Amino acid sequence: XXXXXXXXXXXXXXXXXXXXXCXXXXXXXXXXXXXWXXXXXXXXXXXXXXXXXXXXXXXXXXXXXXXXXXXXXXXXXXXXXXXXXXXXXXXXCXXXXXXXXXXXXXXXXXXXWXXXXXXXX
Amino acid sequence: XXXXXXXXXXXXXXXXXXXXXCXXXXXXXXXXXWXXXXXXXXXXXXXXXXXXXXXXXXXXXXXXXXXXXXXXXXXXXXXXXXXXXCXXXXXXXXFXXXXXXXX
Amino acid sequence: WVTVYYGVPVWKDAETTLFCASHNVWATHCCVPTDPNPQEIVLENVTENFNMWKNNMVEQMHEDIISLWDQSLKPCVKLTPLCVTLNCTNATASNSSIIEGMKNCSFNITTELRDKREKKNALFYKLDIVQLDGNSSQYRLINCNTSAITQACPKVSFEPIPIHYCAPAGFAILKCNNKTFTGTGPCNNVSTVQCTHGIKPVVSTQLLLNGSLAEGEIIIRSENITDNGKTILVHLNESVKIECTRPNNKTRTSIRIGPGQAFYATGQVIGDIREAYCNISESTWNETLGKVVKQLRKHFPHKNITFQPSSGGDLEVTTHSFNCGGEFFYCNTSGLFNSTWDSITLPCRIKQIINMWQEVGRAMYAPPIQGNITCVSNITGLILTRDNTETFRPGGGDMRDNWRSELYKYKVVKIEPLGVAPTACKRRVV
Amino acid sequence: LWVTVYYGVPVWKDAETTLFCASHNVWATHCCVPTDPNPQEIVLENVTENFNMWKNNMVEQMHEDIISLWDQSLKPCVKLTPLCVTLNCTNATASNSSIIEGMKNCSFNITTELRDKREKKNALFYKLDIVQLDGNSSQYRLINCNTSAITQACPKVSFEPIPIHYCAPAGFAILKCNNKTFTGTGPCNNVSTVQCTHGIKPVVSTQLLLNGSLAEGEIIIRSENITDNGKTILVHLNESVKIECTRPNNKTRTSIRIGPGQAFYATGQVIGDIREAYCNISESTWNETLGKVVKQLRKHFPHKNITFQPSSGGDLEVTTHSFNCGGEFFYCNTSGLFNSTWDSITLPCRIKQIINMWQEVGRAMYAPPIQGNITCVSNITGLILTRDNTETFRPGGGDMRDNWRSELYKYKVVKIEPLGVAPTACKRRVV
Amino acid sequence: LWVTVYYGVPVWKDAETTLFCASNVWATHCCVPTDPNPQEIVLENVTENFNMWKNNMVEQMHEDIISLWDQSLKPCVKLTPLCVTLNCTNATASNSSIIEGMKNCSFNITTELRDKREKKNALFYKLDIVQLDGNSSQYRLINCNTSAITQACPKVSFEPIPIHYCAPAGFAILKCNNKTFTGTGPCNNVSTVQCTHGIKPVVSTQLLLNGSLAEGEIIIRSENITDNGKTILVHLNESVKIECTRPNNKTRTSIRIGPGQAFYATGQVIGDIREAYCNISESTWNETLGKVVKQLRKHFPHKNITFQPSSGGDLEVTTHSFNCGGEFFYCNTSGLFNSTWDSITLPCRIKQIINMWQEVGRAMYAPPIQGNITCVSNITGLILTRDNTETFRPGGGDMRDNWRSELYKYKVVKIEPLGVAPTACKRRVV
Amino acid sequence: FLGAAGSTMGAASMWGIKQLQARVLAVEHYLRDQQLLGIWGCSGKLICTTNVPWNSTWSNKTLSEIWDNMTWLQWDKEISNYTQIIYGLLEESQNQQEKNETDNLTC
Amino acid sequence: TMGAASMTLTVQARNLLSDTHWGIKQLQARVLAVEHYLRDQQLLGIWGCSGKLICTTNVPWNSTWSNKTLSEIWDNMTWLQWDKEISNYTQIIYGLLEESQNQQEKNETDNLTC
Amino acid sequence: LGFLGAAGSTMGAASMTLDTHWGIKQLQARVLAVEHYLRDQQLLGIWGCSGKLICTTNVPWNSTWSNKTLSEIWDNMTWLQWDKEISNYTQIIYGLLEESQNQQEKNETDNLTCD
Ligand SMILES: *[C@@H]1O[C@H](CO)[C@@H](O[C@@H]2O[C@H](CO)[C@@H](O[C@@H]3O[C@H](CO)[C@@H](O)[C@H](O)[C@H]3NC(C)=O)[C@H](O)[C@H]2NC(C)=O)[C@H](O)[C@H]1NC(C)=O
Ligand SMILES: *[C@@H]1O[C@H](CO)[C@@H](O[C@@H]2O[C@H](CO)[C@@H](O[C@@H]3O[C@H](CO)[C@@H](O)[C@H](O)[C@H]3NC(C)=O)[C@H](O)[C@H]2NC(C)=O)[C@H](O)[C@H]1NC(C)=O
Ligand SMILES: *[C@@H]1O[C@H](CO)[C@@H](O[C@@H]2O[C@H](CO)[C@@H](O[C@@H]3O[C@H](CO)[C@@H](O)[C@H](O)[C@@H]3O)[C@H](O)[C@H]2NC(C)=O)[C@H](O)[C@H]1NC(C)=O
Ligand SMILES: *[C@@H]1O[C@H](CO)[C@@H](O[C@@H]2O[C@H](CO)[C@@H](O)[C@H](O)[C@H]2NC(C)=O)[C@H](O)[C@H]1NC(C)=O
Ligand SMILES: *[C@@H]1O[C@H](CO)[C@@H](O)[C@H](O)[C@H]1NC(C)=O
Ligand SMILES: *[C@@H]1O[C@H](CO)[C@@H](O)[C@H](O)[C@H]1NC(C)=O
Ligand SMILES: *[C@@H]1O[C@H](CO)[C@@H](O)[C@H](O)[C@H]1NC(C)=O
């Protein structure tokens, strides 16, 4: 059912924070632990993340996450520090545990990926 | 798990079993995951954690023991004509560039 | 000649108010300490007539428990503003299925400011949600058309502690010490105490949990055994271990519905797909019934008997209803009471808006509990209704049975120190 | 000669204490204590005991207990605050004429058991309780809502005038006056001691005292000072005057859900026979009764052509004869009786739904409609008069305490003082 | 050699009980009259141990005051319907400028009818209002998201009257008459009383206003002195006059907020000069403080003492406060306690939403008082805390510390009339 | 406490509202019994003889049949319907004793 | 001559001892009945009359308030008249009764007898 | 003199002895005052006396208890000190007072003093 929107697009100044947000759709934004693909020209690797599901947020593997799960606004948000010009690649948003009930522990990849959008730092 | 799958873009007309086996330092915490794309689009889950199938999967295969996560892709032919890569959902925010094993 | 005596050791049947002696509601209310060295005095050659079915100590316990329960619940969050139409759909699992027994409901709730309403959602148990129209997704909470629903305070524990009922000055409690006493008639071995032993209040239907055990074999107790219009209490001399669990970990969402009015509801469920279940050893249960049957047939000889499931009514009477770690379980006992004359799993349901009292003027809402729950308890007796062959069913009751089964040994009497007797000695004057 | 001390001495003093009552009804529930099936009375010899009904504290205690019970009983009931919305009102057309005169048909938008939903509901209401919001407008509100808490009386509890005996606590006694012509104040030279009063029915009315005691004397006129025009005159009769009050119609009740087990009751329709209410008072009985009252007034007011006039003004509570006829509150016009110079008379009467009841008006009671017709048969046992050359009397009144004072004029409470002080006999019992 | 029993023996044991209150709310509640000529009894050759820090009368007076405060506020107008978004701007005055401390707020409320709404205006203090957004004129009242706010009934001033606490039968109150008593230990000049003297329940923080002055020289009382965590109560033997005022002329309106109930909103401010201020004579303050230091140096000799003005903590801690004419003043004392060892004006602010005591439920709304307000009070003592020479801070403390300064001379004792002593006499005639 | 309750006379030897009601009643019962002993002139005694003769109408059995052979509890039942008679007689005998003590020219 | 009345002293004495708002009122009534009972018993006790409905003392029966008595005439038919004539001195008489008992104790505390 | 008067008196100079919430508190205070009064009276009655200021009984002193002569303990010590100096022997004295009265009740049980 889920139809995550592409992140707000940007053409940021170099080393500007990569501030963007992905509108949520056809999912509970109140659950749905979310992640921001760590987009790159070759392949995304690792992610920034936040979850309404656990009242929590976490640091990115690089730069910063500055992530939030704005369940109230029906949107994912992040603003990684020091966006590199090389960061100008599209990042999809997706979430895990969007279900009413989970048959397993939270140790699985999200599949509902957004069309994505790039920030041309 | 900050290591790549042993992929070399091996491919075939059928049964393109490029089983790179998500060799992510043999420490995926049995949360190996697979996705693939043949388009300028987000990759779709190819397989669920470890040996589990992706929802609405077809022409696919998977296995894992936090290591040696062989994924022969069943006997997949046209279905296998996509770039594909491994990830460890529960370990080091790991991702393998893996390879464009897209026949 | 008449002689006046004072301090004569005699008494009369009497009804008085007994006092209750020892976060926890029971501990908070029954603040009066117990006697660390209680005494019991055997009365040589005293015959006393007891009747557990006419014992006002049972009614007193019933009334005081309800009063405490109401006092405890009263100063808590009201759920009135949540009595709105709900938009409910299928509680989709992470599995390619719908978890049964749950609904995913959304609604427009007024918040702290009266100018704002927000769309909130929560998962609810199917049992507490009622459909407003056929062929419709619109639902209401089950009790919003009948009475107020109040959320129990998360800071208040209802876990029972042993309660001692104590006579006031001028009164004493007589206790029956005949191990084979059946609840009515004379007891030929009695003693006097000031306080009862500690009885944990237990709320349970069908099966009697965490009580005392019988001595001298299993005792079948009834107001009238012949009369099939009355309840039979079976008091066991050996317990049956029962282990109940909820094999999941719930996470909850907090919705503010007023000025500090925090409402809690299930946000998500992580865990197994079985909502709840109870584990009863098979051989233990099978031996227990054989012994119960041996005793039932001494009252109903040369007849075959059978055990059947409860015949009808709502969950409180048809299932085994109990409090497990603050959660409310309604277990299916048809797996036990199905026989004619290694373990057994009883599937269980969970409910959040409950009554458990004959009064429906107010309902309690049980907020979700985080973490997994395991309860181990002792089955000390059975509540049976009798209905050639005889049929016994694990029927319900007025919840007084959970006190009648412990208070059957006690009677309250008034002490009457004055009396007169004849002599042959005229008062000397000056 | 030295002092002897005695205990158990038959001495008493005036006192004010708490009295208790003795026998789904509200009074039966509260005044749960049984009466003495074999009550005693002790006759006193030559005790010129002073009685004063006007200052008698038993009246005030009875008044306060009545108010307390009334409120205690009404409190655990449905509030009507949810109905205080603008009402859209038109003509009530239950009759063939399309007019029923005293009532209006009002529609309103009220929240149901679903807090997010409101529905258009309607009911018939009496004009006496509906307030117009502005001129030339169909927009109305319930009377007194903006100034008070209006609570619906619950059908689950009965209210009727069950006679109640008031009993003294241990250490106290009630003295009773048995002088047939005592007349309110002064020494009563034929008195006795009792533990409980006779049963007094808590009947509430404004002009004519109903279902009370009859006087031993033909008519007795009681006042603090009959020549003082600032005080109320209570006239007790030795004969009952029968009055039959009728509401010759049948109301169809409807029910509006307003909350979680909360519902409002209202008239949905009226079946027929337009006269709203009326009372039948015997004509010949009244003429004789009123003339007898005058004969007694002439001994205080020795003037010819003494007159009677209707209550001079104020709201219905003081201009009409108010009573509870059986769930309905009647406000009847007695100007047809109190108009004279010294087979039946029909008194026009109206029905009201929101009742102030007492002098305290920060709250009000709403009387649900009563299904079926009412024929209340009662007798006048006394009249309440006030006074303005030749004097004029009117059916005026007090603070509704007169209603119990009129029965509690024979009783007073005294404290028993069993310890004596110092009579003398003997010396001292030394060794 | 033989035992004799005596009854009516004038001896006693330390005890705690319930004292009764004897001679608005204060006179209404403490309706019981007092003895116009209390018969104080001097006890020859009696030494008693007093302890003002452990004296439960302080706690009892505190709890009774809270109960009365709440009983008085309870049957009054609720301000629940005012939890709406307020659209606020910068308030003006008869002086065509801006009042820095006031906001002019417009809002939509329920009127007499439930289906109607009206737009109303009211003035509020900056300290009564919190923003719902950043750079946007959207506000709420400060306690809306915490608790209900109840408006005090205008008919009750709560003006302190002397309160006497009286012993119940079987009890007596002992009084210490040592003019240099330090609050604890033996008192070698004692007497008994029926009731305490009349203590006005005056509420303040840093400076104790009103009550009696010390008979002796300035006495510094502390539970420990050495422990910097303890409250130091300085009881002066000479008062300091303090004159406080709100020179502005206020006017108010009345907003119906539903049937029956109405809100006493502030209408307008005219004659605006200063929100509030207090005047303390300079010479008096300097000598008074110097004398306090002279005494502090007897505990901390050979040190040059300084003060640290206004301490730290919240408004209720760092700012002096009192009820003046019904309005609540929050005055800046930093110019009084910044010294090193003709008048000083202390700037002062006003609040409408009041939260005295540690409980923030039942917040009180103080209706505005029309016209201008002046109060003259007596500074009778200081509350100081400690923290290379010693540094002292003015500061608040538990509200209980306010009555410790009045009740330090009194103790509750139970009279024990029965006792036994030797005679060497045996009962006659067996 | 009760001791040999099961013995013959021949062996005889020596929330806030509810709580307040219980305390008050304990006091009322205590005082009622003490007042009654005072009325009979038995204040302070555990055993008090009187000037009222034993009536055969209350019991026509002799002392060897009443004492030694009857349980206190049985005895109270046997004469339960005379308690109010004996008590009335006891009060009057004390009243007569006072009448004589309080006669004049005596002290 | 109030002779017969002495035999009713017992009858009167035995009659002295046997909805939240209501509950308070009922408890107050019960408590006060007890307090009144005990106040009288305590007073008879301090005067040395415990256990007696009728007792005698040694007091001056002072001429400053006591006039000459008569041969069972003065010793009035009505108790309520004495309540108006003798009672005027209750506040002095009760004090005399306590002092007379205090004097008896002083004469025999522990100075005489054993 | 006063209610306690010379509380600080030497034993040798002892001389002789001589609205709902509020409603609940007041009722409790009244009830307790009554209970304390009655307990003292009941306690004296069971020791063989009432109506007395001073009672003499059949109970000897231990003489190990004070371990002092009467000429000092019933002399140079204040009643207030007397209480302090009992040294947790009060319950012993009371038990002994009950035992001696019980012995008297046993000796008076035959009760043959009759017509
Ligand atoms: C009538 O009822 C009586 C109870 O009121 C029974 O008496 C009880 O018998 C028990 C066994 O003999 C005693 O237990 C022992 O008590 C001593 C201390 O008294 C302990 O040291 C022992 O360990 C304990 N025994 C065990 C196995 O734990 C009870 O104390 C005793 N109770 C009382 C109040 O005396 C009578 O036996 C019973 N009579 C009949 C005919 O059934
Ligand atoms: C120990 O405590 C005693 C009180 O409990 C003190 O006694 C008080 O001494 C005062 C004089 O210093 C007396 O003042 C008198 O009061 C009357 C009131 O009506 C006036 O007329 C007199 O003029 C006035 N005396 C003078 C000299 O002005 C108090 O009345 C008296 N209190 C009592 C109850 O007797 C002791 O002084 C005190 N001792 C020590 C060492 O501090
Ligand atoms: C310390 O004690 C003094 C009195 O010794 C208190 O001052 C008094 O305070 C009250 C209330 O503010 C004043 O009452 C008002 O007076 C005006 C006069 O116009 C009247 O209109 C009001 O209705 C009300 O009655 C009182 O006059 C004032 N007394 C004096 C002498 O000025 C002072 O408030 C106390 N301090 C503290 C902190 O409690
Ligand atoms: C009692 O509880 C245990 C778990 O605590 C249940 O054990 C599992 O049962 C399933 C049945 O299909 C087996 O596949 C699992 O391997 C068992 N687990 C373990 C650890 O042994 C047990 O079944 C319960 N009792 C009953 C009657 O169901
Ligand atoms: C009142 O108005 C309603 C409007 O639907 C109508 O159905 C009803 O018949 C009317 N009743 C009377 C008495 O006018
Ligand atoms: C508050 O705003 C209203 C807006 O109509 C204005 O009339 C009023 O004078 C203002 N009051 C103050 C003190 O600014
Ligand atoms: C510092 O202390 C000395 C005494 O040691 C004193 O004389 C002096 O006045 C003090 N300083 C101040 C500023 O008061």
Image (cartoon, coloured by chain):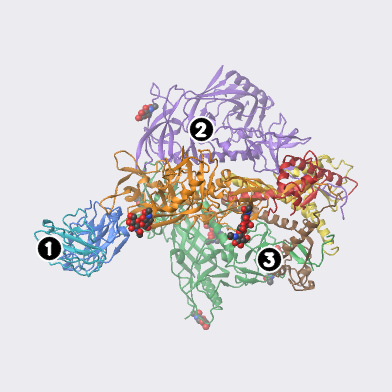
Chain colours: A blue, B cyan, C orange, D purple, E green, F red, G yellow, H brown
Q: Is residue E349 left or right of residue D49?
A: left
Report the amino acid beneath label 2. Asp
- Callout 3: 10 Å neighbours few (<14), some, many (20+)? many
Asked if marks 2 and 3 touch (Cβ < 8 Å), the reply is no
As drawn, the label of residue D315 is 2
Which residue sits at x=37%, y=45%? C127
Which is nearer the eye, D105 or B99?
A: B99
Up-down relation of residue E293 to residue H97 (above or below): below
Q: Chain of mark 1?
A: B
Q: Secondary structure at mark 1?
A: loop
As drawn, the label of residue B101 is 1
Task: Give the CA separation, mark 2 to mark 3.
Answer: 64 Å
- Callout 1: 10 Å neighbours few (<14), some, many (20+)? many
Report the amino acid beneath label 3. Ser
Q: Is residue C113 left or right of residue D40?
A: left
Marks 1, 2: nearer the viewer: 1
Q: Chain of mark 3?
A: E
Q: Secondary structure at mark 3?
A: strand
- Callout 2: 10 Å neighbours few (<14), some, many (20+)? few
Q: Is residue D167 visible?
A: yes
Marks 1, 3: nearer the viewer: 1
- What residue would you read off at disc 3? E191
Q: Are marks 1 and 2 on the same chain?
A: no
Marks 2, 3: nearer the viewer: 3
Asked if marks 1 and 2 touch (Cβ < 8 Å), the reply is no
